[PDB]
Amino acid sequence: ATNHNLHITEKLEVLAKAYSVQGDKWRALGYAKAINALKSFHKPVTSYQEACSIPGIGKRMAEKIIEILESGHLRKLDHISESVPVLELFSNIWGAGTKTAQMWYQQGFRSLEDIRSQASLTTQQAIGLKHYSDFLERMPREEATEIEQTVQKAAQAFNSGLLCVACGSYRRGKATCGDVDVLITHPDGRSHRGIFSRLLDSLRQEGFLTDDLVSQEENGQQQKYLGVCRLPGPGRRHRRLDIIVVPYSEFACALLYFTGSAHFNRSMKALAKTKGMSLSEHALSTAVVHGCKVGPGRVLPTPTEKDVFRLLGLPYREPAERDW
DNA sequence: CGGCAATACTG
DNA sequence: CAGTAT
DNA sequence: GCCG
Ligand SMILES: Cc1cn([C@H]2CC[C@@H](COP(=O)(O)OP(=O)(O)OP(=O)(O)O)O2)c(=O)[nH]c1=O
Ligand SMILES: [Mg+2]
Ligand code: NA
Ligand code: NA
Ligand code: NA
Ligand code: NA
């Protein structure tokens, strides 16, 4: 798939990112969908009218697209606040979002050294800060493989029947991965229970897990672990690792969800909603139960990812095609 | 105009 | 709840 | 930002 509009999307993304770090999330979501619509266009966009014929692109977006197309630049970029580069730096710290970045900025901080020496940091943020560079670079697929295998071997050592699947960008076939997303379950529908505690303690013992970010181990029904790992050996960097354990009945929906992409997911969930259904990482179900939240819908059994697509009347897409 | 995915921890 | 995260 |  060749993005015939790279010259466009490249500029649009700078703006999209600017709105994002400033907290203007809905406006930023709009650009993202516009940007993906452009990447998927069969040819390079050649006119305002044609740009408008594309869903996700309105008059405002079309103006910018044509300006970039015809001038090779977007003047709006020259007007982005000088605070944006700083807000981006701060929000690049895992555990710190736009609100925290803003707070730090207002306090006068402008560099990571400022944050290290004077900023108030949450436990997660302190970990995000010390591993800033490690976490910012995307690791080579080869390393993600090693990480995934490390987790699989440690788990299967407890039960060879356990299925361990690297999801996220690794599953979508990317060449580099921002982190490693591992999903675990068991066909018998019960042997997944209790694996969390044993897996984490096992990986901690061998020194693989170096820090925890999100992990409620007081909960035996715990399904997610967000932490930090590091392969043994010389020169290995620290990497983000997410581990999810789910009962077999939720395997298809968990696999679908954690494979993503994030945009592919919210788009698919939105489609589900229009068909009177609701899609979570747990299951596809009938429309959730005046005009208010209450009870979950009835679950629609889905043994495989294909089943989810089928019940949604959507053509099936391999993981590599959910790159959105 | 209001909605924009559905959900899971932390403190 | 506010914030951040998947 | 866009859509309905
Ligand atoms: C953050 C986020 C994530 N997801 C899903 C779908 C993706 C997986 C993994 O997320 P990740 O950030 O690793 O992304 P990933 O695709 O693995 O890309 P990286 O290489 O990790 O950045 O979770 C989502 O539905 N909504 C979200 O807001
Ligand atoms: Mg990932
Ligand atoms: Na359109
Ligand atoms: Na962050
Ligand atoms: Na992840
Ligand atoms: Na947080």
Image (tube, coloured by chain):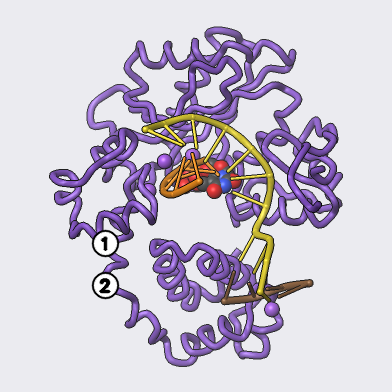
Chain colours: A purple, B yellow, C orange, D brown
Q: Name the residue: 65% across, 45% down.
A: A319
| Whole-percent x, y for residue A60 in the image | 57, 84
| Whole-percent x, y for residue A47 in the image | 61, 90
Indicate the secondary structure of the residue bearing disc 2.
loop
| Whole-percent x, y for residue A10 in the image | 45, 72
Q: Nearer the viewer, residue A104 or A8?
A: A104
The amino acid type, in three-letter code, at marker 1 is Val
Q: Name the residue: 26% across, 72% down.
A: A82
The amino acid type, in three-letter code, at marker 2 is Glu
- The answer for which chain carries disc 2 is A
Quadrant in which residue A230 is drawn: top left
- Residue projecting furthest to the top: A158
Mark 2 sits on what residue? A82
The label on residue A58 is none
| Whole-percent x, y for residue A90 in the image | 29, 53
Quadrant in which residue A135 is drawn: top left
Q: Nearer the viewer, residue A173 or A198?
A: A198
Where's the C terminus of chain A, which quadrant?
A: bottom right
Disc 1 to disc 2: CB gap under 8 Å: yes
Is residue A44 something that shows in the picture?
yes
Residue A100 as seen in the image, left or right of residue A151: left
Residue A140 as seen in the image, left or right of residue A309: left
Establish if A150 lies above or below A64.
Answer: above
- The answer for which chain carries disc 1 is A
Indicate the secondary structure of the residue bearing disc 1.
helix
Mark 1 sits on what residue? A86
Q: Name the residue: 56% across, 75% down.
A: A4
Total labels: the figure holds 2
